[PDB]
Amino acid sequence: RTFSYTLEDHTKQAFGIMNELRLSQQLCDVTLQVKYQDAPAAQFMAHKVVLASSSPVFKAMFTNGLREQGMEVVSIEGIHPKVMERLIEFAYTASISMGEKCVLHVMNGAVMYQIDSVVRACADFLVQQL
Amino acid sequence: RTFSYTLEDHTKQAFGIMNELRLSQQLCDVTLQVKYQDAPAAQFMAHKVVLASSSPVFKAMFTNGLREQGMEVVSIEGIHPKVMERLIEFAYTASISMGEKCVLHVMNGAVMYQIDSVVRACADFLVQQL
Image (tube, rainbow over all chains, first blue to last red; front, side, top):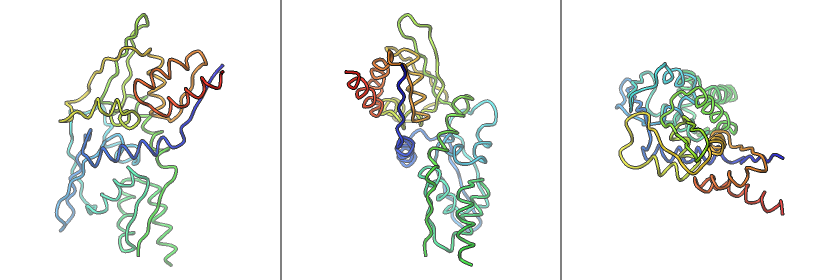
């Protein structure tokens, strides 16, 4: 009496569209403004719900109480823009790529945003290089 | 010189959190107010970017031009609240379930929002019942 269907590729397909929307800067409600030491400032527009879905730190940051009035700007320090870029790309694509010289910095950034999957991968890479 | 990692379960995990946020009514920016013929009105809070990721119709509806001022209300007619509920659940979970008596209505609703995967599944179910 009951009919039930699951599209296994759905979440992959949907994230592809959400990443398209990020890159076309559509429906974005947070701008991450990243200024790290000597490097020129950079900014990244994104969707709070997507960032919250991949990082407990972003989730707590955006779900404070009575949900917000429009596009919010967030100041980020302590992470190089190139690392934040790769973490955002991970949240939107499930993949991350970097040079061996950046693995430590990406791991530092993944710890800062509690992106546990990237922490494990980076930790395991560092240890294999021993 | 280059290290690359993919978390295969990521998009599934992230959608689980986005569905949690929908049900706790956190970070939602659209309310779908559904009034269908005789049935009592119902409303559904959701995330525009998630709905846009699963339906070209919602995507076009929300990406008009200069992105909007806060929580938007959308009036929906022609679909029973129970069908809209199941379509929203599909967008957030990749699964949909219904009784055989509702398959035609769910398919009608999936055509209305161009949720092609649910259209195919419903069409194929109807034809197997022949």
